[PDB]
Image (cartoon, rainbow over all chains, first blue to last red; front, top):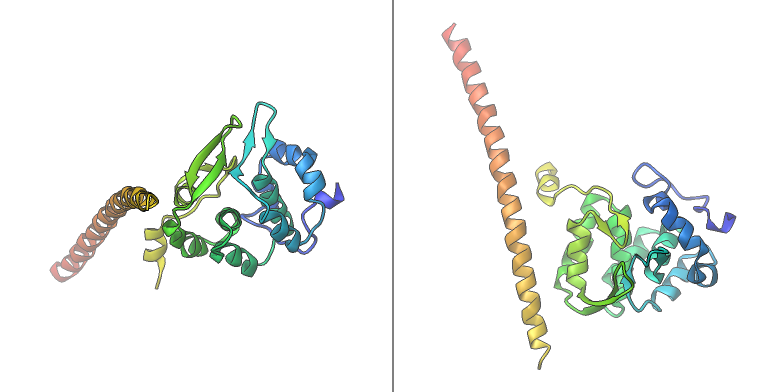
Length: 177
Length: 53
């Protein structure tokens, strides 16, 4: 249970414990999962690097039993350990691993400043590579990176996490000096 | 070769995205312009009042 707690040095995100951005029962299903118990034991950002490179698809939960995908497990792990902006930006900027890129993107959308969200997610609209997506049913669907990015910037919920409210760019620009 | 049509499929997606974002942007432009017009109208009438009375 202690190994599942948010790291001692971590500060609050959007007024709360960063893990609480994920639904209570979703967290519980993650902690219980085979993937989390075997592949997410440890509190290090390097762990996330190694496992992220092994991601084969995006997704949230699937089935009426609410099973987490690896993607969602790593996302929670990231909330728990709160890696530094540098690594997240590296995840995003990297051109070789699309799933790493999307993992960094979702995390940036969940925890970053409005500015950083637009700055780092918007250029990813150019990225039209095909991606594997596991829907709520457990069915695999073809998708494209830029569509995921669009969902991150214009949807209420992605990968079964409710996205924290994000100001429209025009408002942040009108706020600019 | 065939992935040229993948680039074409992206173009279309991006254009839909641009049209949508452009419409939202204009809608909020129009709102802000209206607010500001009202603010200007108020300020002009205030100065008019002071000169008048």
